[PDB]
Length: 563
Ligand SMILES: [Mg+2]
Image (tube, protein in one colour):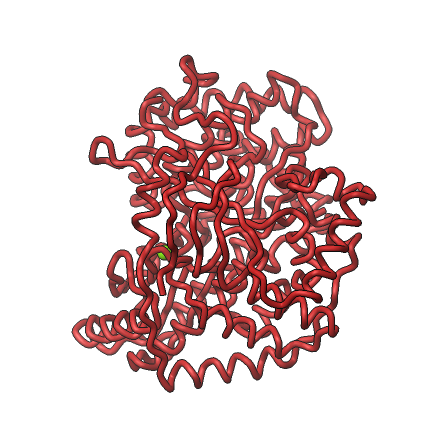
């Protein structure tokens, strides 16, 4: 069937859309080539619509059915709980999109009578009506990027599709426990969202070293959400139904599957009918779990079709990396083509054709790659890094324009050991918080799709527990990483590293001048900036903070707020 059908009504914005950095940047200090930065808007919606609209032809074989049965047997060990209205309400982010029924996220979190009474009626309606498609809103997503190195090369807006707030709270009641527990039960160590960055690199490095002769590849499915078929979504449900479930949870899942997950009408921000979806909606609770299960099922079956040997996969939503035993350069390239042909039959054709890779450091998955540096004792440390271009572009945007979600904080947390996060991101934002005395103020950021409210003065503890003490002492970065960063700073017009070393000293000195958590930030976060390096010992606070559910599951698109 067609992934989408369109009526002609436009994807419209809800308010003014900004597409460029403000006229005189609030921090030309970070980035000088302001014209390189842009944000996507609804103006490019039709370009995205063209890419994402096509007929899916899916052919399932015995390998697919075999793997599905294996997955179901593991799912059948799961017992899932229904969430109470109160528990589900508390998972709603404070700035979640308001309901058309006259209440908003604040009312949901406060358990207001209007909100709670509507949510209860939405729940009963899932039991009373098993078929009527549930309405969804379609919008163009606002995301900031740096322009392609081809003069005028811009990505079009992604299209987000989500149901009303009342429905989203009902999804949590029925499915939050399922999507939080089932993927690991089914996929075991292949489930990527159970790992912190440090644990992910460890799993990757250990997997690499376990092969007599390792070969690895990432597989990029073209527009994964659009490739998800009605069959795939019902197969996903068939896995959920293997859980022990409350009767109303079973029904809610059955109704949500047929009324929302498999497809439905698309309404624009003006309330006009835009058309019809028959693929994955980006903005429902099951999107991350569903994509991960579907990708894992198709890829695992595809490895079997391709006769890849000793495959170990790591799956994060639509992101896939596999490491296996090599059969020779020639036989690998052939196997990889067979794998791609199998994935294509399963309705997951590639964007960029995959390439066998015989150096772990050259594989990028989840936009990231493994690289190597050295700690104080000169011991080899592996860490995850990425090209810093998008993080820096978004940092510049967030410095110049007010933003609800602070991607720079998420990046500092997730990439704390990197050369660019330590020298640029940390230096830049700590100077800003220092100047405005906003240091103590908690900020919103996302980790694996879930929203968290985090105090920047807690970064030392967070980083140590997540990445290890070596995150504060890494030196001797790889030539490839140094050159990638240098090239990035050239392109964006970011001042040279040596310069950041200077600003850092000033910041470090000011932080120490304050004492307390501020002083701890000075000592640990900026020890790279001095030669007379303060000896760094494990912080007392590291081990005694609530980092429980930070790396349990993926929640991208699921409207989840943690703590
Ligand atoms: Mg893809």
